[PDB]
Amino acid sequence: GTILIDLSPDDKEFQSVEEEMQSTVREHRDGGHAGGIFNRYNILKIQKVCNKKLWERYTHRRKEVSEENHNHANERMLFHGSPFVNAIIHKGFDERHAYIGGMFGAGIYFAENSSKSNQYVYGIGGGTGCPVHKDRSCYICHRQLLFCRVTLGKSFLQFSAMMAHSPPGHHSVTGRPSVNGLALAEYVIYRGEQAYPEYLITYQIMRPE
Ligand SMILES: COCCNC(=O)c1ccc(-c2ccc3c(C)cc(=O)[nH]c3c2)c(Cl)c1
Ligand SMILES: [Zn+2]
Figure (tube, protein in one colour):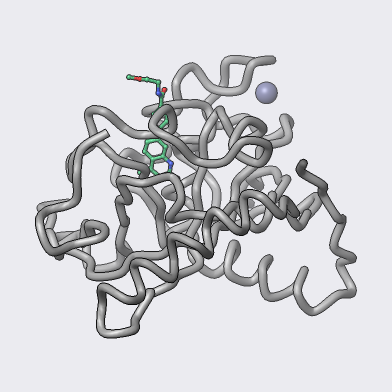
């Protein structure tokens, strides 16, 4: 039931989405090992993901979290990178998109830094890089990220020195780097229904000059 609508680069929605991409790149402590070396992206396409069934699944859960949290969904827009992006846009987030060995427990991870999500585009740790060149820093091959609507409800705050249940009380976990003062948060949900993949972003990382 999914349809994809191209946003025009002249459209203001294309532009605020690109801005959130570009403005949340940071340097990474792995020197670019997982996601490659770059400061900015070349944005190639931005599509809006439309699936009535997945949307209702999301808003139905959103209402429930909302009611449990002093009428507050605590709804964010957050990046998600994964080899399973084409499956997510068609069938939604589920247990199979969960990071079993994740630091904040076994759920689905999202990132405020788009460059954090880019590290996972070719799998945990960048896997072996693009399918074509086996290059985690490939500047040629087209990559895809999702920019997603995520319901956090009451988030459990977990300071970090950088499918399970949420801790009782909580609808999600915030993993908040405490050492790297420029690293933004990651969040973990334990139910697929708590994220909708609104935008599919197709891009290349750009070689620095
Ligand atoms: C035991 O393996 C079973 C198969 N599953 C995967 O191969 C898998 C699971 C999770 C992820 C994953 C992880 C963490 C992030 C974070 C932090 C940010 C983000 O944007 N995406 C993530 C994506 C991946 Cl790539 C693969
Ligand atoms: Zn490549």
